[PDB]
Amino acid sequence: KSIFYNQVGYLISGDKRFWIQAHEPQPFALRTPEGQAVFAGMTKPVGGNWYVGDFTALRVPGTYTLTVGTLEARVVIHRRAYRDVLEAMLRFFDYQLCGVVLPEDEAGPWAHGACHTSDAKVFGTERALACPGGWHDAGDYGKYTVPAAKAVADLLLAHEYFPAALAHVRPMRSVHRAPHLPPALEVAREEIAWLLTMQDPATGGVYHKVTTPSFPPLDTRPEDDDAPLVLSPISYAATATFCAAMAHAALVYRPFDPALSSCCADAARRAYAWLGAHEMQPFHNPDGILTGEYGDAELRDELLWASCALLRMTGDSAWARVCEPLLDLDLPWELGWADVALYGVMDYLRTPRAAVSDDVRNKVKSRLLRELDALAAMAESHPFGIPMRDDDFIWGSNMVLLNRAMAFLLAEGVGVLHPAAHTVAQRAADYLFGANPLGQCYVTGFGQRPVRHPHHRPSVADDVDHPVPGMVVGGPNRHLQDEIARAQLAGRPAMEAYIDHQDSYSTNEVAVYWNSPAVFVIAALLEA
Ligand SMILES: [Ca+2]
Ligand SMILES: [Ca+2]
Ligand SMILES: [Zn+2]
């Protein structure tokens, strides 16, 4: 028996919900710490085990004691409830920084020295080049181009959608170059910078990843990882995904860093030149390389995104000839890392409408709305109001949820205003912060049941008891895709297929592209 709620808190002007397992309505009260009832209501069935208590009408800020039946809970209402968790979600990218000293005054207990500072050998050859900076991808120390592109795209979109909300947030500012950019762009730049080093000059092609041949033990501190670095071969996926991220960066950084902006635009055009002279061949790990593959068989949604990004970057109507036939395809319109068509949809919809066929544009917006309707229909049959169903609870189910909430919010910028856009965004935050069958807050160092044991090298390696805060875990994975999950979570419903265990990498790992949609969604909720 337990009350299920958003354990970070609620916005004064936001919807306020709690969940309980019950088979009957039942009264509830919210109280000041001294015990005085301030709000009273009745619970409502959402089926089957689940009942819901709505306390949206309570607009007074403060800490409240929520009581229903014989259960009690600590509830926080604040005009800016999600500020701290937002900062921490953004600061995570700075905690992931490679090849740069993280001082104790910024990083606290999780401070460390500049790691992976050696040059990397181009696979097969005897050449070696520096690819320093950027982010450790996930629980490991690999730096992969494809998932990196999603991470930067999300942070750039977050800045240009919700700059005011991100302004209240502070990164590891002293680690970064001065003058200091807005928090989202400041963080994203390190990664845009690492990444420009990943492009082969005299080809324009981009190396798929820079990793050690295999994973170090879960014990390895960032700077005890002294295995040689290798650059896996140039891939179509990495090149096209690089092209779209750089063309995106070229636009956004224009008023902040003209030199970076111009450098990214030229890098994007060179990458697209490579795509036109090469074959859409899926990446596979070369022999001897055992790290994260980030493979993918479909590369048309990558070409789509790369084409639409250059369409918006240039405003040149000539790009629409390439983009629009690709937008017709029955590709899933998703937000990566493998299926990136929706990013292309967004750059095309945000392109000035004069440089674009208005007939195709209406079809694209019509398909987007119909989808949003499909996601809305899922949300209204789910007890927790999230656009999910059992089969969606796969590896990184939290990202699946966050991307879908992001899709509702992105669409508001292109004239597609779905009525459920903001309740879904709130329900997504609630679920992520504890409103789920496990009562589990899926972010490290937050809520009343925080993630304690993430599959995260620096968190496992250190003698620090608490993990790096602000890390969003993958979430419930029905496919039980690691030994711990198999032995422990067999036969439980999809939403309970999670264990806070450090060896459960398929349910409890972190990722740079799992934090990036979280930053977008939380920044959306903060900006009213
Ligand atoms: Ca793809
Ligand atoms: Ca620790
Ligand atoms: Zn490193």
Image (tube, rainbow, N blue to C red):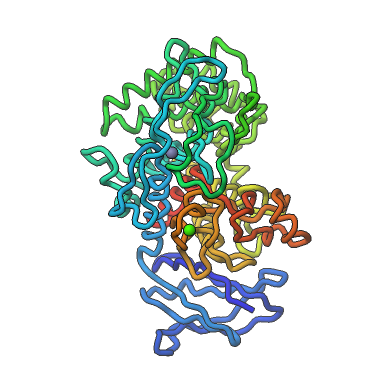
Left/right of residue 312 with respect to residue 486 in the rendered view:
left
Does residue 458 lie above or below 433 as drawn? above
Q: Nearer the viewer, residue 398 or 484?
A: 484
Quarter occupied by the C terminus:
bottom left
Q: Nearer the viewer, residue 420 or 496?
A: 496
Quadrant location of residue 381? Answer: bottom right
Residue 427 visible in image: no
Q: Position of residue 59 (x, y in %)?
A: 39, 73
Q: Residue at x 45, y 36 (%)?
A: 153
Left/right of residue 47 with respect to residue 82 in the rendered view:
right
Q: Position of residue 448 (x, y in %)?
A: 50, 70
Does residue 416 lie above or below 500 as drawn? above
Does residue 346 lie above or below 102 as drawn? above
Q: Position of residue 462 (x, y in %)?
A: 46, 54
Quadrant location of residue 48? Answer: bottom right
Quadrant containing ligand 1 reads top right
> How many numbered badges does the structure rendering display?
0
Quarter occupied by the N terminus:
bottom right
Q: Nearer the viewer, residue 364 or 474?
A: 474
Q: Residue furthest right?
A: 491
Q: Nearer the viewer, residue 211 or 512?
A: 211
Q: Residue furthest left?
A: 179
